[PDB]
Amino acid sequence: DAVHGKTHVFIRSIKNGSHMQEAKIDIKSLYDSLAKKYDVQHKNSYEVIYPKGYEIKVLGNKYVKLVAMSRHKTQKHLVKIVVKSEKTISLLKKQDEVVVTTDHLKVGNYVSVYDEASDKEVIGEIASIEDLGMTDDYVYDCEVDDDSHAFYASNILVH
């Protein structure tokens, strides 16, 4: 389990105790940015950043600390997951998509989805899963300060 670099995440950063900024940013962009600010630890093939004063939106539509972030090359296939939701406004149908790696979730399962326009969490259904094949690109991982161990990845809750 990692996510593709174009995965979107909701990030808050804090400075000087008193100032905070929040934005929706791609995870590769977040990584490259933090790479200038902090610096990478290394394991067998992981490059890891332990940022301070960063937070990420997770289950419960709340921001918790982003404790670490990493990237690595992977042998695993990229898998595109499409998730549908809807609300009555008269039906507004929505879908979101996230590309993850995994060696391991099922079409038909329900998953939590962040409805950004109404700033609330809704139930989504996995509508499709597609094997996109192997990749040469880096894939990314977050550790989040929440016992859900999950964060919203392009509006879809992922672990």
Image (cartoon, helix red, strand yellow):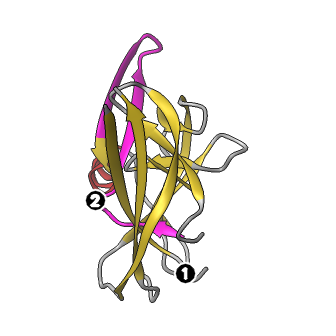
Q: Quadrant of the N terminus?
A: bottom right
**Secondary structure mostly seen in the magenta stretch:** strand
Q: CA distance from mark 1 to mark 2?
A: 24 Å
Q: Residue at x 29, y 43 (%)?
A: 25
Residue 22: image x %, image y %?
Answer: 34, 27
Residue 147, numbered label: none
User: Element at badge 2?
Assistant: loop
| Side (left or right) of 123 relative to 24 | right
Q: Amino acid at mark 1?
A: Asn
Residue 132 within the segment the image draws in magenta: no
Q: Which residue is mark 1?
A: 44
Q: Position of residue 3 (x, y in %)?
A: 42, 65
Looking at the rendered structure, which numbered label has been put on residue 6?
Answer: 2
Question: Three-letter amino acid code at disc 2?
Answer: Lys
- Magenta extent: 1-24
Q: Is residue 35 left or right of residue 40?
A: left
Q: Secondary structure under badge 1? A: loop
Residue 103 drawn above or below residue 12: below
